[PDB]
Length: 122
Length: 120
Ligand SMILES: *[C@@H]1O[C@H](CO)[C@@H](O)[C@H](O)[C@H]1NC(C)=O
Ligand SMILES: *[C@@H]1O[C@H](CO)[C@@H](O)[C@H](O)[C@H]1NC(C)=O
Ligand SMILES: *[C@@H]1O[C@H](CO)[C@@H](O)[C@H](O)[C@H]1NC(C)=O
Ligand SMILES: *[C@@H]1O[C@H](CO)[C@@H](O)[C@H](O)[C@H]1NC(C)=O
Image (cartoon, rainbow over all chains, first blue to last red; front, top):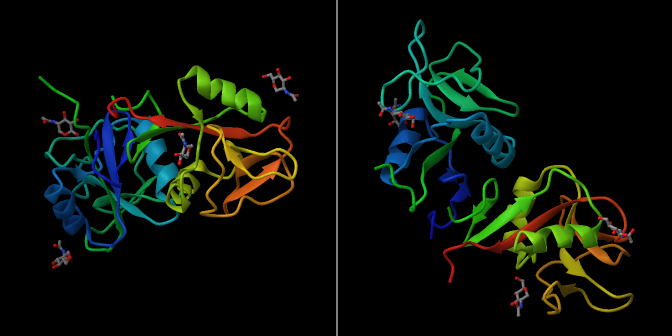
């Protein structure tokens, strides 16, 4: 199977949409336990898939920042600015129509992403 | 890739959700051209997944009937009653409750499904 059971496949990745709510760091610890990360949204097409599937509640994704800084990926590098992220918060999430930001201690649903099983990067 | 580009993978199948609208027979022709069929919805659970992604438009699916007669999948097997397909029409589609039906010449979006390329 390209993706784990109950994950959703889309363009060489596998996505998990949570049932539970957790804070941002706890959501990342959950994704890390599944050999994945909080969604690393790398194109506008991926964004659109996520907004369409997720349904009505806010979902954490894997971008964080410091107040006067750029948004960073989980690996600590500045991200590629595929879409605007609104608000004045430290952790990013998806809402009804796009990406916004809030404090990392708030409990939200989350999305994990990883590569499908047939992807090689060598 | 398990699925062709932009199809959504779920539980060893791939699903195509159209952006365009067609009548039911031409929708099944599109699906067949991409080595698939109009979605042969297998169960209430598969239903809940298609309902999650499809968004507000009506989408044709792979069941139809002759007047009076039981619903049949594209493959010829009679529907197994995991949920009702409502209405008075010959051709089935998904609204946001579950399945409803209409005249086959009208214009709706559609969903295709097929087994992913690693099934065997
Ligand atoms: C996040 O939530 C956990 C319980 O899930 C709590 O123990 C932790 O202190 C909270 N905040 C952070 C930043 O870990
Ligand atoms: C860091 O993570 C991002 C998001 O997946 C990836 O696109 C980028 O190539 C990675 N950068 C490094 C230096 O590993
Ligand atoms: C017809 O398709 C349905 C829905 O997936 C499946 O349950 C049934 O086994 C199929 N019959 C054959 C012969 O493919
Ligand atoms: C359905 O549409 C196709 C064109 O894609 C056409 O050949 C066919 O006549 C239409 N069927 C009906 C009943 O209007």
